[PDB]
Image: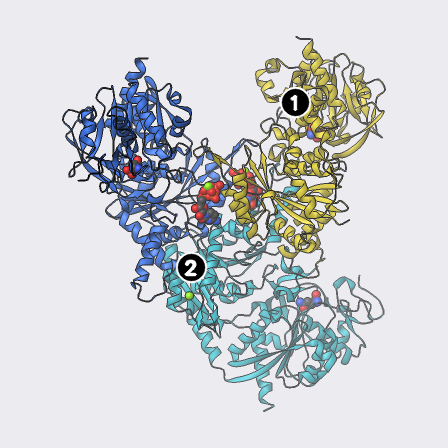
Chain colours: A yellow, B blue, C cyan
């Protein structure tokens, strides 16, 4: 079976929903039994998003194999059951960095190294490596048709299409169709002009996905076809919907996947969207409501927490509980006190870097342990909770993480090789990716995950200081999971509490709307339980 | 006194507000004491909008000199006091038409006649004609930058800018900066792309006017400036507003007029927007409310009645009355009956052509003459009033206009050449025309003068031979022309407020100066509303 | 005094003569007493041309400070008396390589690193560093307006222009105006369309330089002005000329520099072109003719030898001798024998890498030493001559350079740390840039350069093997110059010959048409002397 490529580009503006549109299309194809994958090409110069603040392009997502990648890969894994790896995300930086290393070491045998063919060859090679043995590969191109930064990407895929042939390649282009109040109509002009820009780069789109805040009527769809050399049936409307889970069914109901299977000549059964319809049904029919406070330092751009917010939403689905997520600046806790935590059925403290806003989290971890409000702490949020417990229950004054005050008396969280005592004695490298974790026989989480061993994903360097550990266990705190070797602590529980769990790994990256996640489902159940005993 | 041009263009999408934007800008400049004018270049092929359906590009506006032009000229006249004439509007059709004629007749001396320089030359000459003897001329280019249709307009102005010089020309380019809900941001990408299209046609914009449904924040303005080679102070924000009357003010508060005066080297006092401030204040503080029904055949596209809608709103201002205009399909008076006129404090029947829906208008004029509801009838509306009368009070069975049923026994409205009687016995107006007011009419009063000037666009007149008969049965002749004493205004004098006229009074109404008929009409509608 | 920038771009095609057009313009400005410089921006990905074969974009030029750069810098140094350094040439590779190194080490503080502003900032910074304290800086942009590879360059300079203002920036754009035989006219259409491409990138050219194979008449110049928003007087004609030395006077005679000085507001005296007129006069009035054979492995692209060919031409000027340069494949010597060297008044063997064609050079060095035909050997050509002498006069059979047969018995040329005996005994890193060299008291070259110490430029790694040196001196060969320390051999002479010199340094990079070069002038004199005793 020959591999087919659908290239996804966007025009007019960015924030158009390319990731989500691609992922949804992939979900449909998946449900026709096709073997599908997706990859993201980002135009940034960063070698990988590992050096990007979460308020730049949102969360740094992590795949099983430890790659730091764009958050689109989160969308991909939540719409299809394929696992993303390093192979599904690369940037312009990564391309240039490979080519420079090869040029400097003489691999090009004295040739002038050029954007074409050398940069573009490099791009084609990773596109082929990401597609390897899949029937259909959606290749999402970042940036907007017309700007400078994504031109080599577009020229690469142009070349591929000619090389591979139109029998096995399609171009899917998203554009904006804005509504004008004065005239009461949506406008095709930007689509017309975007398609001319795309053509001027040498690409004829085959399918047009029309983004608007309402459906694009037949009249205007026909106008777009007329001007873009695309048949009417390949001009698809994609309105703003109240739930992303509806997107696959919306695209299916307009023939998009039929049109694709015909072009690629695949006999495949009609997409069965039962799992989506189920998720949609669940979402539409909550039995009760909770309010969960997410308390962290990046709430000014919520995408910093994209996968967490979705995991919560999946926790809602598994409990038929509608989760109202209220974002709370953890630094306002420092200023305005515990006051602003009033009125919450649970509390989540997410991950982060840098001292700013961390003392507000420690406080937040406290308030939730003392008032018996259920608490989930992820990475940093597990670290600030160890810190809370030590300071306030094992009475280790001023305890902290070497990340924030390097020279503190009780460094409860520190790099493995910074580990020391309160006396100064010692014993005689980012953790990335999927790692096995042993669950402790009598813990909440051993029951929730219901297995002695689980696999979750890491992105952190600061560990639980084993040298100060016994002193904290002795004061009540329980260790609920450890790694495979060198027993580092992965999970802690405060057992005098309805529901208080915190973990080092990012469980949100393995949560999905179809299959949920045992930790979040638990966390949300507890929030509902707690909500109902206050009423 | 060198003449300065400001070329106004539009990018991304149309329906951007170029007309109003340009008109507002003009309003500010006039308020600084400058001699100013505006003109519209339409890319369409119609020689003029005279053959255009009112549901196509809206109403056909008529200027003092009797030209039929785009409705944008209405906006112009409602923002500045300079009078538009036929030189303030021309189409691509008009341009090719003149060049073709000159060519078939040999004026090109056997040259190959080309888009450049012959079509572009013809465009340049007309832009110069519309501009002559003005300080600042706003030239509004129809269509959207990027499209085929307006390229010759764009190349002609590019040439003009280079000929006349950068010290006397400015390019103002409007764009759309849409809001994305996903990100909570307005987006400058389309502006950056549109300025590129404009540059590729050889035009560097000087001023960017950013349309959006909310203000464009300083960050986005700064990014537009960085990418488009314009300084930040020349990136202006023009959000959707709740009242066009606030647009002169909104632009002036961002320094637009200063920027222009600086570039064109003019010392002019600061703009005095007091009349606009007054207009905004009136509109913001109505004391009563009314519902007025507009009954006619083009309600599917409200711009068909653009100047009438506005003249009512100006009637509102002058009485501090807020007017709700209920657009009513007069075809529905035919199907569903007089019920659909339930709940109106006044009824206006506007102009039109074609029989479809006119029987509904006659039922409508009756309803109002009968149930003592105030009525204003413009052109068709005045004609269908006479039909109602003769037909229901002078008992002239099935009376009509020859435009609709040519061989009717009683042609009360008919071309002047068609003028007959009930036995068969015997014996198109455009522009500003003098009208004489009858000494004892509700209208000699409202206009507070003997003779007036109003604008015509119609063929069919009141039949003078059937006239003395309808006068006897009650009806009153309130105004008449110069010669042939044709009937211009009729009143039913046993009604609180019933006026109807042949001319289009809406074309002279402005928000600053109001209009005596619509002031009158709206005042009456208020008085009626109080009595229920 | 404020720095002014003239940006030079090209359109329609490449090979348009941007380097030469810029350099000539610089020469005019120089002659108005202005302090001028020039820089080249290349769109290649190579970090620097050090890894490019000479048949890629021609010779790798070397500046005093040792930078490996584009051959345009040769043109610059031959038209103005400023010295080029690393500062005057950078590539896209160099830009990306700096930015990647800074991004990976966290210098961007978590920002997304983008083509704009990060790549473009980097470019602006080197443009400012190259311009530092000069009155006028010509900034030559490589590639052709309209292609992908030079877009960031164009966007950078666009930004600069707005920032610095039009008071101190001009855009000079070259285009092609082709002659059509069918119609008998030159065509302005490509200029029209190129200027629209340049505008679409956001740059309004200020000056148009019209390349054609004949002058561009007034009619068409006016047409170009009409369509490009440029005044007639800024549309300059630049026909194919028989001598580049005429280009400054051609541009001057059309007001180009007047137009520039007016725009930048400089009072400067009229350009005095006396030195050029002199060079032109010299060139036009040769007294006799010679034929010099250039024998090397890259003659398929003569630009591989750009500066050598020009040095010869300057040697012609200093002797009023018209040099007919005949290029000869040194590999055809291997095949067709010494035969193809018949009919030559001198012989030059240039530099190179790799064994292919080197045995033909050794042979060539031989033929010239035996028949007393004057010989100049540069770098490789000095190495193959040591090799010739050893094999055939010091009778060291099969002698060679470790570069070619690493394990040979007599490695006469080898890396310093490969140095060994014919017995295998030993004693108890490219050379780049301007280095001092001591001249030997009784040598030809000590007289020609007329000083005990000279400065010439290196680009080589293989040295004269000091361990086998005494054995070659003993057989006749004389050392004519050495370095400063560690006495490595820079120059050799065979003293039983009318004129036989060879050197390690590249003397062609310090030769110019105005001031000539003592070695080449000598070499050409000798060729003329030799030509005249055969007649
Ligand atoms: N490449 C094109 C496409 C359309 N037009 C012109 O576009 C005008 C219509 O303008 P507008 O409504 O702004 O364009 P639409 O195509 O209707 O797009 P939208 O849906 O945005 O209105 C027509 O007169 C037609 O001649 C043009 O000149 N060149
Ligand atoms: N001519 C341009 C302009 C911008 N960019 C790229 O555009 C990206 C920003 O994308 P986006 O936010 O979509 O564009 P903005 O310029 O911010 O515009 P908007 O207001 O629509 O976001 C940057 O990485 C920059 O490299 C580009 O490649 N070419
Ligand atoms: N993403 C996170 O929460 C990281 C936590 C902490 N700063 C660490 O590096 O270990
Ligand atoms: N504009 C109109 O109302 C036209 C009225 C009528 N059809 C006429 O021609 O006289
Ligand atoms: N440019 C050259 O001639 C180099 C000569 C020789 N291959 C060396 O590296 O020393
Ligand atoms: Mg339209
Ligand atoms: Mg942006
Ligand atoms: Mg021609």
Mark 1 residue element? helix
For label 1, the crowd category at 10 Å Cα-Cα, with few meaning under 14, some 14 to 19 and many 20 or more, is few
Q: Marks 1 and 2, Cα distance to the nearest angstrom?
A: 66 Å
- Residue A45, image x, y percentages: 62, 44
Residue sitting farthest toward the front: B423
**Chain letter, disc 1 residue:** A
Q: Is residue B55 visible?
A: yes
- Residue B289, image x, y percentages: 34, 18
Is residue A129 shown left or right of residue C109? right
Is residue A120 shown left or right of residue B260? right
Mark 2 residue element? strand
- Residue B480, image x, y percentages: 18, 33
Q: Which residue is identified by label 1?
A: A284
Name above or below for residue A13 compared with residue B368.
below
Name above or below for residue B50 compared with residue B343.
below
Name above or below for residue A268 compared with residue B101.
above
Q: Which residue is identified by label 2?
A: C207
Residue sitting farthest toward the bottom: C535
Q: Is mark 2 within 8 Å of ligand 8?
A: no
Which sits in the foreground, A66 or A422? A66
Residue at screen point 61% across, 60% down: C66
- Residue A328, image x, y percentages: 60, 21
Image quarter hosting the C terminus of chain A = top right
Q: Is residue A350 visible?
A: no
Please report contact status of discs 1 and 2: CB closer than 8 Å, yes or no: no
């Amino acid at each position: 079976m020959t591999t087919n490529y659908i290239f996804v580009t966007g025009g007019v503006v960015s924030s158009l929903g390319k990731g989500i549109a691609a992922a949804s299309l992939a979900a449909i194809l998946e449900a026709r039994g096709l073997n599908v994958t997706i990859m993201k090409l980002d135009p940034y110069i960063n070698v990988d998003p590992g050096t990007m603040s979460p308020i730049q392009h949102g969360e740094v997502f992590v795949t099983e194999d430890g790659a730091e990648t764009d958050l689109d890969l989160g969308h991909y894994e939540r719409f299809i059951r394929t696992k993303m790896s390093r192979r599904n995300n690369f940037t312009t930086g990564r391309i240039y960095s490979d080519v420079l290393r090869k040029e400097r070491r003489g691999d090009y045998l004295g040739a002038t190294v050029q954007v074409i063919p050398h940069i573009t060859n490099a791009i084609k090679e990773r596109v082929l490596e990401g597609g390897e043995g899949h029937d259909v590969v959606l290749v999402e191109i970042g940036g907007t048709v017309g700007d400078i930064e994504s031109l080599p990407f577009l020229e690469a895929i142009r070349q591929m299409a000619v090389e591979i042939g139109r029998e096995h390649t399609l171009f899917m282009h998203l554009t904006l169709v804005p509504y004008m109040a004065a005239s009461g109509e949506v406008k095709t002009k930007p689509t017309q002009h975007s398609v001319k820009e795309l053509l001027s780069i040498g690409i004829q789109p085959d399918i047009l996905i029309c983004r608007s805040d309402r459906a694009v009527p037949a009249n205007e769809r026909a106008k777009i076809a007329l001007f873009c050399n695309v048949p009417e049936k390949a001009v698809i409307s994609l309105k703003d919907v109240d739930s992303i889970y509806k997107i696959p069914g919306l695209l299916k109901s307009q023939g998009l996947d039929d049109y694709i299977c015909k072009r690629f000549s695949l006999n495949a059964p009609e997409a069965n969207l039962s799992e989506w319809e189920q998720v949609i049904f669940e979402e539409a029919n909550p039995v009760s409501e909770v309010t969960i406070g997410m308390v962290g330092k990046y709430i000014e751009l919520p995408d910093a927490y994209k996968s967490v917010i979705e995991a919560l939403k999946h926790g809602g689905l598994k409990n038929r509980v509608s989760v109202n997520i209220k974002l709370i600046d953890s630094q306002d806790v420092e200023t305005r006190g515990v006051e602003i935590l009033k009125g919450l059925d649970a509390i989540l403290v997410p991950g982060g870097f840098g001292y700013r806003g961390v003392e507000g989290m420690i406080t937040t971890a406290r308030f939730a342990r003392e008032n018996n409000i259920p608490y989930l702490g992820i990475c940093l949020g597990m670290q600030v909770a160890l810190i809370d417990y030590a300071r306030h229950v094992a009475n280790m004054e001023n305890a902290n993480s070497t990340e924030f005050v390097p020279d503190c008396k009780y460094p409860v969280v520190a790099l493995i090789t910074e580990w020391r005592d309160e006396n100064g004695n010692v014993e005689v490298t980012m953790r990335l990716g999927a790692q096995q974790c042993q669950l402790v026989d009598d813990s909440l989480v051993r029951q929730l995950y219901n297995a002695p061993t689980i696999v979750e994903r890491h992105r952190h360097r600061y560990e639980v200081n084993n040298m100060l550990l016994k002193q904290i266990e002795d004061a009540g705190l329980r260790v609920a999971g450890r790694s495979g070797d060198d027993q580092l602590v992965e999970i802690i529980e405060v057992p005098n509490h309805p529901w208080f769990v915190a973990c080092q790994f990012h469980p949100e990256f393995t949560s999905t709307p179809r299959d949920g996640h045992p930790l979040f489902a638990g966390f949300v159940k507890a929030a509902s339980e707690f909500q109902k005993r206050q009423a």
